[PDB]
Length: 54
Length: 55
Image 1 (cartoon, rainbow over the protein chains, first blue to last red):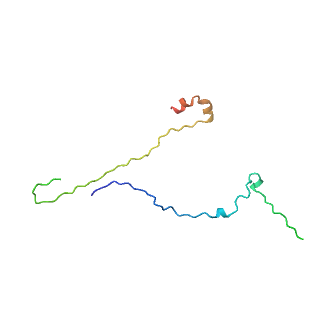
Image 2: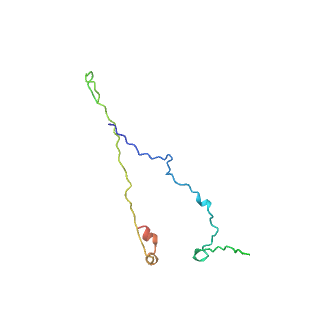
Image 3: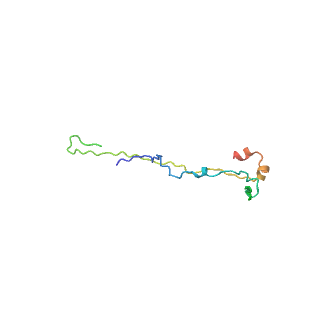
C-alpha cells in the first residue's frame, strides 16, 4: 500500500454563524440628558410644566 | 525486483512508495522571574542593569 503524508487543510467558505440584526437602538430616544455625573444619585430631574383649569 | 530472462513465470512484484513523517512540537517555556519590594528597589538595588538584568 502506498502511504502519503498530507496536511489537514482548513478553509472558510462563508458559513458565518448566523445571528440577529440590530434595529431597536435607532428607534428609541437616546441621550436627552447627559449630566448624571453632576446630579446626586445619578438622577436628573425632568420638569413637566403646569396646566390650569378655568 | 528481478526475474530470470525467458522465464515462463511472468509475474512482476509491484513495489510500494511509503512517505514517512515526524512531528516537531513547541512545548517548553523557559523563564527567569524576579520580584523586589519597593524598599529593596529603592535601597538595596544600586545599579539595576548590572545587578538584575545581566544575571
